Amino acid sequence: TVPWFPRTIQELDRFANQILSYGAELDADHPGFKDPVYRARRKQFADIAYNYRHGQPIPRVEYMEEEKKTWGTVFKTLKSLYKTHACYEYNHIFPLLEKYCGFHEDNIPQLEDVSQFLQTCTGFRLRPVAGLLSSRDFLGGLAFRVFHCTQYIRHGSKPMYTPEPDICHELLGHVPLFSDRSFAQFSQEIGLASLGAPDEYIEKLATIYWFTVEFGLCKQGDSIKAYGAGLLSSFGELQYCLSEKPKLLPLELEKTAIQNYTVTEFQPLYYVAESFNDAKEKVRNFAATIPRPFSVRYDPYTQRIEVL
Amino acid sequence: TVPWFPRTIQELDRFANQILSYGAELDADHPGFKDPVYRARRKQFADIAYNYRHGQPIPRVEYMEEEKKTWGTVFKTLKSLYKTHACYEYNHIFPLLEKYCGFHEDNIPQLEDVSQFLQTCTGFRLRPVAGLLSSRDFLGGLAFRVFHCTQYIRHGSKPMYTPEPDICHELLGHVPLFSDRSFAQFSQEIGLASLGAPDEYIEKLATIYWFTVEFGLCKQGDSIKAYGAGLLSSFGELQYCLSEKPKLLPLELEKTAIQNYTVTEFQPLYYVAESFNDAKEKVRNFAATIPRPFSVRYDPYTQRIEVL
Ligand SMILES: [Fe+3]
Ligand SMILES: [Fe+3]
Image (cartoon, rainbow over the protein chains, first blue to last red):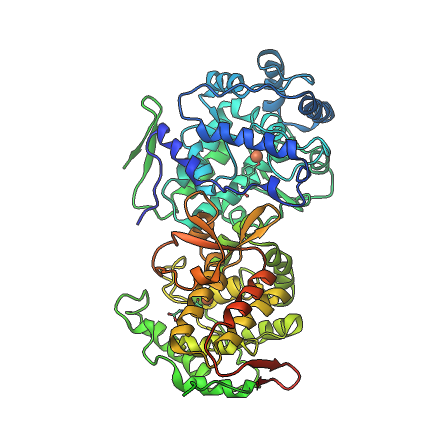
C-alpha cells in the first residue's frame, strides 16, 4: 500500500512528529556534549521547530556573542574562496544576500528574512527543523519548494568543524542556490519523484541528492565549479574538489543512484552536471522508472499536489 | 520430571528431529507460496540444515542472481540508518564485517565465514536451522554460545518484507551484536537460565528475549540507540522506535517477562537497557527465581554444562 505523502503544503506540519528524537548533540563525541549551556540552547531551538506551523512567520532569535563569533569565523574564512571556486549562480546572488538579508561577519541572518527573500526569487521558503527528518519527509518538502532548515549553530570550540548541518551550512551552502530559478526547478523534481515512491527508491533519490545538491560540481564555460552545499560550506573540501586529486565522472543517474559514499572524509569522487536544466531533465526521466501507480503534479496556484 | 536439556555442545544435534516440519512457506499468504522454484529452493536449504552435525564446516551455497538482488536492495536501504540509529557496538564492528566477511551489496556472506569470525571475537558460532525450533531448544543453544541461523532468503517479490527470519535478518540484525563480548555474555545468561526450566518459565524467558535481543533499546551517552535484531533489520520500525511515538520503559524483568506483544505491527512499547552488563546481571538475578532443583555452569574448556 502506497506510503503516505502530503497533498497540500500545510500537511508538511505532520513531519514534526516524525523526526529522530535523540539528536547528535547527545552523543559523547559531539563537540558540545559536555557543555550544559549548549545542550540547553539546542533544546531551545528544537522547541521552536517543534511548535512551528505552516503560515507562521519563523520566530526571530537573539544569538549570543559567542554564537556570533563562531559565525564570523566561518563566514570570513569561506568567503575568500567563492569568487574562484563557487559557480556563477552563487556569486551572482551573494551581494544581494549581503545587502538585503544581512549576510555579514557580525550578524547571523534571521531565517524569516531569508525565507521572504527566497520567496521573492523563486517561491522557495524555509521552515525550521528540530532534528533529523527521514529521507522520505525531507525530499517530500522539496516538492512544494519548501526547504527544512536548521536554526542552531555548531559548538564554538571547533568553528571549522561540524558533524551535522547547522545554520552556517544552511545559509552559506544551500540558500544561495535556492535563489536560482533553474536550480529551484531541479531540486523540486527530486521532490516530486519521491512522493509515494517505494523505500528502496527513496534511498536512490537520497543518493542522487547527496551527489548533486550536497556535493555537486557543474560545468561553466570550459571550467568546472562547485554548487554542492556541502562543498560550499566546507573550507577544506572546497579547495580539494577543484584540485587534481578527486575522480570526476559525468552525472548519469543510473550510476549515480547506486554509488556508495562516506560521510566522514573528503569525497573520492564527484559527479559533474552539464547544467541545472540538464540535471532537471535527467531526474524527470529517472523518475519515470520509479514504480508508482500514479503520476503527480504540483499546482503552484493552490499549493496542492494533483494525483493523476 | 525435569525436562531434558543438552549437556555437551554436540547434543545440540538432537534438535533437528524436533522442529516444526510444516514451514511458513507452505501457507497461502506467504509471498512465495505460488512460486515452485522458491518452494524447491527452501526445501534445499532445509535439507542442508537437517543433515548438518556439530563440528562440520557449514556448507557453502551459490546464491542465484535474483537472491543476490534481494539482498542488495535490503542492505542498501538499511545501511543508510545505522550511523544514526544503531548502537555503538554495531557501528564499531560493521566495517570489519565488510572487510573480512564480505558484507557488501553484491555478495551474500557465507555462514561458515561468518561463524569463524564470530568464533574469533567471542566464541559464538552459528549452525544452520531448518524451520522453527521450540523456544526451549532455541534458547538452550545460547547456553553454549551457539546461535541457530537461517540460511535462506525472503522471496524477491517483496524485498522489504518478511514474515519470518531470513538471512538478511540474521546477518544485518543479530550477527553484529554477537561480536560484542558483553552482549555475548548477556545472551548466554538467558540460555543458561533456560536449561531445565519449567515450560511456563521458558515462555517468560522467550518474552524477555523478544524485548531485548529482538527489540531492545539501550542507553548510550545521554542518548538512546537500537540494538534489537528485529529493529536493526526493519527499515520502518528502526526509524519509528527512536521517534516520539512509542512508549519507553526501563528494563525491569519482573514486568518485562509478562508483557504482551504483537508480532505483526510496530511495537507500542520498548524496554531500555542501561547496558548489556547490567541486563546480564538482571537476567542472572531473575534466573535465581526459577524453580530448578539444581544450578548450571558452562565450562568453556570442555564445552559441557556442569550441574550443581
Ligand atoms: Fe545540507
Ligand atoms: Fe531474530
